[PDB]
Image (spheres, rainbow, N blue to C red):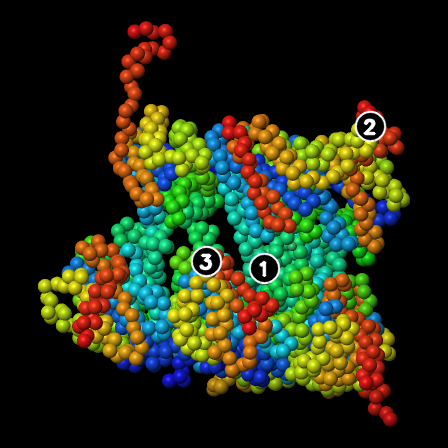
Amino acid sequence: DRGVSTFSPEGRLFQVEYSLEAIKLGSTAIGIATKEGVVLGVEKRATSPLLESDSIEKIVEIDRHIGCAMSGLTADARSMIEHARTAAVTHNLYYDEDINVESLTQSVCDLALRFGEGASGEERLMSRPFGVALLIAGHDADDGYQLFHAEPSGTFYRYNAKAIGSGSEGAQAELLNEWHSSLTLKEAELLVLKILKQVMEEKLDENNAQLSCITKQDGFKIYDNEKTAELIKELKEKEAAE
Amino acid sequence: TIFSPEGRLYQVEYALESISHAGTAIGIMASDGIVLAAERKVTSTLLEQDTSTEKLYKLNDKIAVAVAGLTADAEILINTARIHAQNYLKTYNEDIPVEILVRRLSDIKQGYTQHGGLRPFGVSFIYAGYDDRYGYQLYTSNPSGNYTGWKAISVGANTSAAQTLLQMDYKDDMKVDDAIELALKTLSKTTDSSALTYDRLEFATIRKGANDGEVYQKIFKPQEIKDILVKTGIT
Amino acid sequence: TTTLAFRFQGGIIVAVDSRATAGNWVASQTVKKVIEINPFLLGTMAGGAADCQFWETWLGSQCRLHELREKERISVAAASKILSNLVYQYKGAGLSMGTMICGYTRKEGPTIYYVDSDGTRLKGDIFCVGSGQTFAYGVLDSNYKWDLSVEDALYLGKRSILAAAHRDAYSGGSVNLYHVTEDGWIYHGNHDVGELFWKVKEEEGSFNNVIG
Amino acid sequence: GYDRALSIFSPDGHIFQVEYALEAVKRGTCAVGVKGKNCVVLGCERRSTLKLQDTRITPSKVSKIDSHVVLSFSGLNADSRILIEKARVEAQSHRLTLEDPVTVEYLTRYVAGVQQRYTQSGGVRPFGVSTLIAGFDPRDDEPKLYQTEPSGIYSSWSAQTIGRNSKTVREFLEKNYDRKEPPATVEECVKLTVRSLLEVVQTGAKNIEITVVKPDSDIVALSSEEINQYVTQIEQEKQEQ
Amino acid sequence: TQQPIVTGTSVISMKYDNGVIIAADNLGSYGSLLRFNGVERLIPVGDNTVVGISGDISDMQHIERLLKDLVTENAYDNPLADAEEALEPSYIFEYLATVMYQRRSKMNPLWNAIIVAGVQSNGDQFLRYVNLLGVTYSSPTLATGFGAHMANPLLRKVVDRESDIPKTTVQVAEEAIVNAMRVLYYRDARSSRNFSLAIIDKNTGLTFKKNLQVENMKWDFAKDIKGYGTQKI
Amino acid sequence: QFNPYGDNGGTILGIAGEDFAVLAGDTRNITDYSINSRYEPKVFDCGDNIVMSANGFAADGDALVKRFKNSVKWYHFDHNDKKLSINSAARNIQHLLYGKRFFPYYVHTIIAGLDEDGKGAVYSFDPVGSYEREQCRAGGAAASLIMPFLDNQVNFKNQYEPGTNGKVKKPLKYLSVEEVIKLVRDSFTSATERHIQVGDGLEILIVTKDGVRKEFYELKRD
Amino acid sequence: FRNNYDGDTVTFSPTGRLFQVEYALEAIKQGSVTVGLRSNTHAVLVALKRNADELSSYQKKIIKCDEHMGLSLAGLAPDARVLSNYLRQQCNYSSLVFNRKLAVERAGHLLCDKAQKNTQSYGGRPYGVGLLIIGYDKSGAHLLEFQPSGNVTELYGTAIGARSQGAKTYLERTLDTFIKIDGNPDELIKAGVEAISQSLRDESLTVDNLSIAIVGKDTPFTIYDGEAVAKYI
Amino acid sequence: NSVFSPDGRNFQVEYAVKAVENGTTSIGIKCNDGVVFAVEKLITSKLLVPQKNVKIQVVDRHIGCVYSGLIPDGRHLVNRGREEAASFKKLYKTPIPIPAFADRLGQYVQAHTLYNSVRPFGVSTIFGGVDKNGAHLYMLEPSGSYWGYKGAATGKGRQSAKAELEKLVDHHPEGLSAREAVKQAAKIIYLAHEDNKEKDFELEISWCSLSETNGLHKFVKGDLLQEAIDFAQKEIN
Ligand SMILES: COc1ccc2c(c1)[C@H](CC(=O)N[C@H](C(=O)N[C@@H](CCc1ccccc1)C(=O)NCc1ccc(C)cc1)[C@@H](C)O)CC2=O
Ligand SMILES: [Mg+2]
Ligand SMILES: [Mg+2]
Ligand SMILES: [Mg+2]
Ligand SMILES: [Mg+2]
């Protein structure tokens, strides 16, 4: 052990790589971007049957037009959410408009860069990288529906579909086959629910898994338990009949 | 500051280890007073007894401490505790309740445990105090910043040995004079020296002020310790 | 400026003029003195135009932030206290604002808070604020009953701003009217004093100090 | 000052200092909480290493954060005091600005945030503490119980336990806590809480302490005699077959 | 809070067909004491720019150092410092305007009025003014102080609008400058018979004339003036 | 004592059409009773089809325009070349102005462009950032001369339908760019006649769904 | 030897090497290829963007710095964002204060000095990104290459990133032809698109693969992506 | 850095010197009224724009600097030198004397050998110019050490350059004109290129002369450069 921002001989940052490892141990989070909205789903993964599952917040509202899903050391995600909300509200204060989704993501990624001391060229107020990744989903007038993956490396990518966390290698391959540009919101809802069902260690019901989406017309919504239950009737019957 | 794989704090552990080599201090709380007795660490004939105080310190008129550990660390802490007591007096026009002063002192210790990469203070304290909420009180604090209340307690060397003896003879209905005896007997039994002579002791009481309605701290002159070592029959 | 808000049987009436002045110059007749903070919260503005517009827009931002943080709408009490506490930080720097925070929540019921730049914050059933306040108070107080219909209460509010627009050189333009309910503000229109005065004179048979 | 990083990532993705912080909680005395239909009960075990204590003045393990919210912990005792102080301050500050006492969820989010902060700041070590926060929201009869841990993760529980041998008592509570049927009253909720501790303590003398939280700022500690009557009744009734 | 001490009166200037002319007298006043007489208030920067300064002379000397430092600094790691990356009048100006405006915004002004004259690299005339408040403007003619009230009216008879500038020759323009200097010497109690003058021309470059004197003054008519009304002798 | 403020004269006027807007200003810059320049523009193309003038103390006007042009540049950088819409420009300028609340800019500012629907839009600010969208506005030295004319000739105020015994008002129509330029020129020749700080030149900036166009007219030089 | 000597940037190896800096240089070699080249009238950047998946976007390699300047990146992308932001600030400052477009050369010096402080301060890493900077200024088209060691060099053409050695050899060969490609934007781009081809073990470069940027005489710096590049594949 | 070896040495500085030896070769020559500076620029590829990666740097108006080793470390040193010369002029009005300037650089370089949190500089710098009392040439090592020189070289060609420099001191004890020193500088740079011949090189020369440049620092360009290149080409063959 020597430094927190040392390069390996290959040219990579040790601590950045390992934080990426903390994310692989997280619950699963999946997002799919259609042309009728963007769905975001997560594995709740209660550590005991005595834990009250609806107290598990892994999907949060950032603004009316932007939601996000987390995977990893989820406590690290509080200050990122706080920052994201402030940036969006502030942007609306300064400019009387909605912040673009891409701009919001870039701001969360700038925050993530701030580990160290002030790295001789400015100032870093945080001792390690974040141990959590985010899927950032929303709508804006320039670019429509969008899905971003924000990493503790401060890089972000847009994705037609994306999975993060423990089941992510497997879920991603699945998404590579199922995703096409044409999907309805309902088709995409079902796909998230299907792919979570595959990779989860319990039987997926309306307590260990959570759904949400964002549409231009209704904003960002976290579906209540009764609604998801009725989509889980619906998936069961669609597959049992195929 | 760092944690061990066991979830223990090295530097704190090692500071407690250091304290177990220091002279034993004993505190006993009775119903009408408190006793503080301490053993001075292997002395010499030439050491000035008449102008010495290494183990017993006055915090205000109603609170005293017995020290086990590095004296120099203790003086740092004692001084801040004295200031803290006066701030309280100035703010509220009331003498500081014993617990409050103990808690503040403990919090300063806890701090060194958690941030700043300085070493902890190698000090353990027994506080002897009176206030009008809880009457007579005895508390202990160690380098971790933890503190606890007691009817009788010891710190420094042979605490385990001294604690068992106190457990045995301690009774709730005790007068201070019985506590005086108990403390001297317990140090006598647990010394690593021939006998417990006056020149190796510090002794203090917090009584109900002879005949008054008021609280008085008596810090024993060497002469008094020699005389009180007579009564209890250890010559 | 004249602004008022009062509580009655069927909620809250909020009414404001729309005149902006610098000295004796009439800067605008069409200024917006109500801020719709959220669907259940209104802010009224008197004093420094900029001071009011800026800090009440800002208050909107802070209110939205509370919603995201607490997954619940901010209480009238707490929204008003944010603005109160901000303004108090600035005491003695020359901020100039008289303000009403008006809204509904389940827990509070319909509520009005008056907040000014001296730092005063009061809860009450009736407030008139601005250079025209005394005029508004005269009409409002002498015709106010708790049990007024919604229709009448809307009229009285409308009629009190008109009173003030007429007598106070620094009020006028138009009335902007709002009703706040359980559900909860509803806009009851912009009414130009130009037309409203003659119409009220005709129909009510009042304003007899006026030739014509 | 000194802000050299002590809490950093392991090759396999853990933060070692936080993980070792959990170890300190494991060796701390046990603490448990369960929620009734109209109450919540907090139980703690006091150690037996030293028994010449003065119970009048020794800081007990359940702490009032406000008049309607309580906090207990397992782990470093000195560490807990920093959390209890900040929580108390935050609670007064929230009454000052929002003109309302805190919700139990709010207070938890707050403590958890403090814990999280101490896992990512240079020159500080994480809190060797996990907490149970229990009480009722202003003007609400629905009871609340939350758990925090050195990472800053937090969540609600019908019942939960922390500290040494928490594993045993957790197991006990999973078998014994029925979600449809919460303990209908105070008396029967206290009993289930005592039963879970008896699994770990082995005599429940002055070593088991109980605190009962009822709606609208009604919080009472229990005496020796009130606890003794529970232990007596439990072991006698549960011995026959 | 500050107040000028040693000052120096108008700076006057105009554009002609090929370049610019700027002039200023050589006096530094101490209130009504005509204190110092060799004061140069025309500051050549490179050879395409002259900065003319009036107001407080201590501040003037400060702005001289700033301009010299500016030439040094532009030369650093700049192989084209005496060609395509030479300081232009517009860069010198903008810089000074920035300093001027920042200093007033800190309530601590440089107590001056400044005219920047020169020719840009594309042959265009540059003439612009900045003062202690950071106010800036440009005109075919520019003058500070009394020069504003008395030189401008005269100079404007020659160049009254943009379309007059291809029509004005060096000779005509210099004549108008020299004459306006004489009028200022007649009527400004803080002026001096000695002045400097600079021409910056797209062909000729920089001609800097020193130790010029107001000539051809009319004073003879003074012998006929007796009394203040009725007195005859 | 040092006074950080001055007064450069100067009058500006904004009118919104249906699918155009204009911002006009005289080109004369004054100090006390002297003329600094007869041609110093104070209406600016700020990019994104927004024009701006900040009139009063010219050093504060320049500073603000500069600062806002810079806002537009950084908006592109930070928001992937997004066009800054007129309403968003307005809100931004409010923060610029209000940021100096305790050491203000001595300007009255007007911006003009098209809104989201391509309607002509005009926004005007007091010196500390209070703002409003309006069909038209005059600002600066001769504002008190020109505004009431505009109230009468743009919004037809106090004009009734002949014969209706004053009930039917002249109905509020939209004005062509030709009619608007006519009112602008007349407003300024009026102001030049009666205000000593107004004259020399008139520069008009016209904004349409094809950019920004410039027009110039001589004014009286006395 | 590489043993105790690569702990930080604040330590020389017994050979006089700085391993942290050499390791940083290694992240550039990992980054996707990019090419820059120029003639007398234009400068062009060409970059191969890299996706993280077939479901993802190809991440951007070109960043605009001013109207006359921008750069491409190879290495740590967030490091590119820090430096381009600083460069945007330096460009801006020069415009506001001096009304001067920043020389591409000065932009080099500035980036170099910034990289340098990070090769010498305890507790901070060097930058792990290479940059290719193009601009048009008062002495024409320019291309620069920036290494995180702080070494910046002016070149007619060059390439950085993985497999970039092919493209470089091609440009070394083509030199005397592309240098004269004047007043023909499209031919210069074609030469850049061809140069980048010599660096593909990959695939046939697609409408997403390709990022092109241009700046020159009468053309602001502009970025082409997606459909607008098809006419070059 | 702050670490002394058991025999009083500083290994980090010794290692910093290795970075210098590894560098390109550069020289300076003191003449009768001035100083001449020259440096070898390795042409890595034909793509390098000729004449356009200037290594010689000016400080104030009257001082040239050349260095070998890590180039960024030299630029850092010159930035600091420029600040230090500005501060001198601001207070004392006169441009900084070369000995004064030397010590400013000296004290700064030496400072970076006192603290464990800093590395020494990885350059040797050759610098000088004309002041109130003549011409001066200096060389500054990573340790902060500096002395006045008649002629100086550093970098890879250091040994042969010094040998050539030593000859001139012997043949011309009566002072070397500024125009002669220019020629000889071009020659010497050629005669240290021998070593690094694998790749091509380009020559840079600058001078500061009382009678040839008015005591200002100037770059040798055009006909003077070509003539000095010819002298060296003819004297190597
Ligand atoms: C340097 O120049 C300065 C400096 C400081 C300040 C001003 C100018 C300002 C100039 C200025 O007066 N600006 C005007 C203004 O604020 N007018 C006030 C009355 C005057 C007033 C009353 C109390 C306190 C301040 C001002 C007004 O109309 N208030 C009613 C109203 C309420 C809400 C809304 C949305 C609009 C209007 C606007 C309308 O142009 C005052 C100020 O703070
Ligand atoms: Mg917009
Ligand atoms: Mg006029
Ligand atoms: Mg050291
Ligand atoms: Mg050497």
Q: Nearer the viewer, residue C113 or A15?
A: A15
Could one spot residue G212 in this view of the protein?
A: yes
Q: Chain of mark 1?
A: F
| Label annotation for residue G217 | 3
Residue B27 location, x and y as percent? 58, 76
Q: Nearer the viewer, residue D162 or C209?
A: C209
Mark 1 nearby-residue class (10 Å; few <14, some 14–19, many ≥20): few
Q: Nearer the viewer, mark 3 or mark 1?
A: 3
Q: Quadrant of residue A236?
A: bottom right
User: Horizontal placement of D207 versus A24: left or right?
Assistant: right
Q: Which residue is depicted at the point 73% across and 63% down?
A: A216
Label 2 is placed on what type of residue?
Gly
User: Horizontal placement of H149 versus H8: left or right?
Assistant: left
Q: Chain of mark 3?
A: G
Is the same chain shared between marks 2 and 1?
Answer: yes
Residue G21 location, x and y as percent? 42, 75
Q: Secondary structure at mark 1?
A: loop
Is the same chain shared between marks 3 and 2?
Answer: no
Distance from disc 3 to disc 2, alpha carbons, whole Å, reads 66 Å
| Label annotation for residue F81 | 1
Q: Which residue is depicted at the point 82% across and 47% down?
A: C179
| Label annotation for residue F163 | 2
| Label annotation for residue D75 | none
Q: Are marks 3 and 1 in contact (CB under 8 Å)?
A: no
Label 1 is placed on what type of residue?
Asp
Residue B108 location, x and y as percent? 55, 69
